[PDB]
Amino acid sequence: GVLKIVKVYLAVKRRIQPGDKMAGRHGNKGVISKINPIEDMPYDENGTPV
Amino acid sequence: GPEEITADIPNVGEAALSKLDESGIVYIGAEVTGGDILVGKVTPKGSDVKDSSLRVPNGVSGTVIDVQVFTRDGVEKDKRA
Amino acid sequence: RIRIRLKAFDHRLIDQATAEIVETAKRTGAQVRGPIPLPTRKERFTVLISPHVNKDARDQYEIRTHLRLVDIVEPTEKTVDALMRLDLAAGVDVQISLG
Amino acid sequence: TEFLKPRLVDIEQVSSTHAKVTLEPLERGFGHTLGNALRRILLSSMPGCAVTEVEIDGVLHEYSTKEGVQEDILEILLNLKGLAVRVQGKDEVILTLNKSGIGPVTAADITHDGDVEIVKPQHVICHLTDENASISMRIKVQRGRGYVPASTRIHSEEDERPIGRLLVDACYSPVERIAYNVEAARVEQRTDLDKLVIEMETNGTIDPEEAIRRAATILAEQLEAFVDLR
Amino acid sequence: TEFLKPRLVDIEQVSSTHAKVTLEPLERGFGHTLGNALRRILLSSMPGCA
Amino acid sequence: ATILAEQLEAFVD
Amino acid sequence: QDVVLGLYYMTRDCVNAKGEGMVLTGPKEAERLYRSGLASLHARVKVRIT
Amino acid sequence: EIKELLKLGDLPTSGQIRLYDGRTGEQFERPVTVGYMYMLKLNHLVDDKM
Amino acid sequence: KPLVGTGMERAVAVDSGVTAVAKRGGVVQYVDASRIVIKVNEDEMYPGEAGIDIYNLTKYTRSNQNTCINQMPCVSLGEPVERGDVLADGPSTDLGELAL
Amino acid sequence: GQKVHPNGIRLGIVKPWNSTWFANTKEFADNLDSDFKVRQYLTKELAKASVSRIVIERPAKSIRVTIHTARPGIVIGKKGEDVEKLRKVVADIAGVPAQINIAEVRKPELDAKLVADSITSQLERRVMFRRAMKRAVQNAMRLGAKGIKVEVSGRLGGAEIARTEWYREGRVPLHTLRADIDYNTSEAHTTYGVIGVKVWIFKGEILG
């Protein structure tokens, strides 16, 4: 029956962006709102950003 | 008549023959997005030609990782088959 | 001392090459002599431009081979070797010569 | 106006990467101002070189696999994105890595030129297992700032490049972690002065006094718009 | 590696003791740098007599 | 602004 | 939800803080004392409001 | 045992570290909780819904 | 690798057949670009059919929900493995555990 | 034979060279020959692929080819299958290590050579030359050429008496050296004889 059978496999690589949905294991749903720079993050006194 | 797998895509100009070979179909790999052409697949009598050539959907990008073809015993040009 | 003879047809390219070489020299070693411009070879050619006959009909071409003489006074351990990995842009024939 | 001016008095290198630096003397209250301003600038806007385009021979896309290696090609591109290069003269160079034989492929196997310096001679990239396997990649190292990703650099690139060059994301900033502390200064006649102890953590490629000088010039030339015009 | 210098676009002078210095455009995460630096200096370091 | 610029006037290029 | 927590932490009081029982000539220098680091956000104080 | 394991590492026993702000450089009052939660990315991506 | 797990990650990541659990124990030859090649220890090895086990790794392919199911070898060359041990980490697995 | 070649007059200023290498009087002729060979081969191979400009560049006893083509997909084929194949043959032709790069030609209607080739093809498959010419001109204009000229000559419509016809549109300054004038030529080997196609495409003036 079917004559011309061409299947093409794309592969998109999606990163993360304002609007995706993340969640932990406990039921804490979330839509990631702002993708901040590294500088504006709350850093502890050791220097590492959260 | 039957439809055809050829790059000789009509009306549309030097924006059809690009991510493909001289005998038609997407040439594998590449940074394809939306509105591109993957498999030239259009018939004559369908100055009466058209564009059913399966393209890339709107909004998606990607890399052609694999092309499978168990087509109608004939898909070949003069020899890739 | 390392004498370096840069030769090329494009002058800008040659200049670029020379600068690069100087940079390579100057970080590792010390007291680079300098990029001294030698005379350019203007090798001219006349040819008849007709297929058959018309002798006063002529084109006069030329190839301007430019020379750059870069010298390095103190060859250190680090400096001389640095050029091995440091290849220059294409269309520039270099010619290093120590002593 | 009884103000003073600070200087970089002591610059200690705890290691080749993690290195503190003092600043002395600062006026009263200025410590957290200069520390937070230099933190924001030193984390956002520093120039550093990174891997941009990787060109492996006998490859179609980045999601394939190769003969004789461990890490797959996405793993190789991630391990190359972590690389730390320090060029001097040019702003765009092309390196070469060629190696055959059973054993891991360090970063010390890249056939360096004169003006490029690879500061991590134990950075692993591949694990070649077959002795008949080879790998010949040609890396391209640009120089910029911030974060410019593959999607935006998919049409931004003007110089029409040929097809087959894998595009790696560009993490240009060589500063990863910075903390400042406002101590009490040991001034022999003043008690109301303080020192600023900036504790940088670099990529190994940036020189800390040069980084502080560049961040200070960035801040001064940004404030010149307030100084001159109104 | 070249930075965006701004133009001071507005001094909306509300009264003789009021201003609003609209100022654009800066690099991403530089408005907070300039604003916080000027604010701390103007609060706790500007000379004067009373 | 000129207070901060003269404060940072030392180690610039 | 977030904004009522910010208000309930802001307009509250504690029996001792920085600047307990000092006197302030207006709300503008109340915010100036909070920002410079000389009083606390909840510290009971006679102000002069209009 | 969580407290005792937080004492084996050199971390504070309460689980809470004082954090500064990346914008203003000044300490958040009343120390906040920092830790490692195992967060998942669910397959409800925003550029399949737009 | 979840830092706070329950220990049931191992059983789920093995028992769902997304990882290439070794059938017969032994050493390894590790051609692996195409397939893990495991030399079998003699006690688990049949008298006839001399035999070394060649595991097929399923590289980048389509799942039912358009995600990517991919297996990566987590054992090096010349390294002992036992029966029931894992060899190739599937999608969302890290050394035989379960990393969603 | 009135006119100077538009590429040739501008090589020092606005146009660059195709073969880009240095050699002494000893090895120069040989190099040239090699270039001729490789180029010829490439033309033969990538006829169906729309190829504009082969740029040869040989440093350090190793030849670097750069193929400017409108559709890389047909020249590359499957990722690194066709290119690789090409490479070894190139090397053989040269007698040195080969390296093929493939530049993607944005806007093949504005590339002159490509246009010429297209026209030739059209002529070969028995279209009205005039209509083809019009198409060529129009398309270029649409694409954003500051101007274009095309000229076709000899045995037009199989006529006994040969003649030349040409269509210009926009501005095509040839005396102006700083003008980016992409010139190129082709030849239609028809049943009645050859039909030569010239085409000038003016991208714009360069300021330096």
Image (spheres, rainbow, N blue to C red):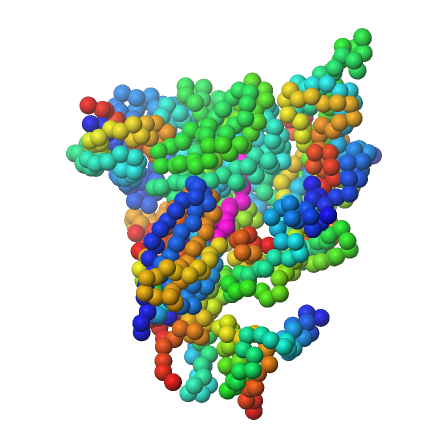
Judge left or right: residue B76 versus residue J88.
right
Which portion, as a residue range, is magenta?
A: D159-178
* Residue at (33, 30) in percent of width and height: C82
* Residue at (53, 82) in percent of width and height: G22
Q: Position of residue J20 (x, y in %)?
A: 35, 33
* Residue at (46, 45) in percent of width and height: D18
For the residue pair I43 and E10, the one nearer the viewer reads as: I43
**For residue D115, which quarter of the picture?**
top left
For the residue pair J202 and C70, the one nearer the viewer reads as: C70
User: Which quadrant of the rendered structure holds the N terminus of chain G?
Assistant: bottom right
Q: Position of residue C24 (x, y in %)?
A: 30, 36
Answer whether residue I13 is visible to the viewer in this image.
no
Q: Note whether C16 is above or below F4 in the view shown.
A: above
Q: Which residue, as the protein is rendered here, is positioned at the far front?
A: D188
Judge left or right: residue B54 versus residue D10.
right
Q: Which residue, as the protein is rendered here, is positioned at the far top?
A: I48
* Residue at (69, 39) in percent of width and height: A9
Answer whether residue D29 is visible to the viewer in this image.
yes
For the residue pair J42 and I30, the one nearer the viewer reads as: I30
Q: Position of residue J194 (x, y in %)?
A: 45, 33
Judge left or right: residue B12 versus residue J47.
right
Judge left or right: residue G15 versus residue D172.
right
User: Which quadrant of the rendered structure holds the C terminus of chain G?
Assistant: bottom right
Q: Position of residue J134 (x, y in %)?
A: 49, 49
Q: Main secondary structure of the magenta part?
A: loop
Asked if residue I68 is among those painted magenta in the image, a careful observer would answer no
For the residue pair J53 and H16, the one nearer the viewer reads as: H16
Q: How many marks?
A: 0
